[PDB]
Amino acid sequence: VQLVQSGAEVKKPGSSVKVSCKASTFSSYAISWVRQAPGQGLEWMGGIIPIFGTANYAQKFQGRVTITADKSTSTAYMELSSLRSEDTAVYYCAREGTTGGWLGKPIGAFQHWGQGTLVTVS
Amino acid sequence: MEIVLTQSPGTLSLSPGERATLSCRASQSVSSSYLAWYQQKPGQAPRLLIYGASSRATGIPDRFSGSGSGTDFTLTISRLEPEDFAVYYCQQYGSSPSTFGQGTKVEIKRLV
Image (cartoon, rainbow over the protein chains, first blue to last red):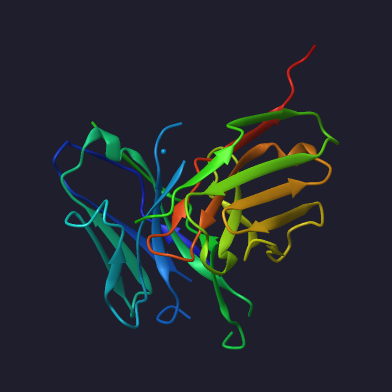
C-alpha cells in the first residue's frame, strides 16, 4: 500500500488547483483529503469510497472542493477553487487502515498517507 | 455540528527518559471511542500511533499507550526516546466531519 501524490504547485489567487493521489484494493476503501498550513496543524476536507463514486465533504469547503476517483488508474483527485492565501498548505491524501486482504476489517483511522502536495497561493 | 478537539499543552519540553503525557479534550463525547493519535516529524507525513482510543497500530512500540473515553483522552509515552521528539495530533472519526486537535509539540528541554 503506497499513496503517491502530484508535485508542488504555486497558484494565483482566485484560480483552482487539482491534486492527484495514486494508490499502489482501491475501490473498496475510504480515501480522504487532509491539509496543513505553515506553522491550523491538520484539517479534514472530505473523502470518497471509489466504488460508490460520490464524495462526502466538510461543510467548510462545500461549494469549492471537488473530490473524484478513477478505478482504472487507482487515482483519487481533489480540486479546490477560488484560491486564497489562507489555502496555502500541504494537502495530503490518506487511506484508512485495515486489520488485514479481505480478512481485514477497516478501522477508520488513517494508516496510510501520501507524501503530501505543497500548494502555495501567491 | 463538528466536534472540536483541543490539545494541551501547546508545547511539552522534556528530557530523554522522562514520561510524556499529552491530553485531547473534545467538545462533545466521541462516538465509540473512535479516537486516534498521530506522530509527525518536520517535512514528513503523519504516522498512526493509536486507534480506537487505546489500540496500538502495527509496529508501534510498547512505550506508546492511549486511554480515555467520553471527552478526555490521553496519549502517554512511558519513557521518551530521542526519536520521539515530534508533534502529536489527536483525531476523532466517530462523527462527520472527522476533526483533528491542533497538535502538541514535544521538544527537548533547553540547556540550564
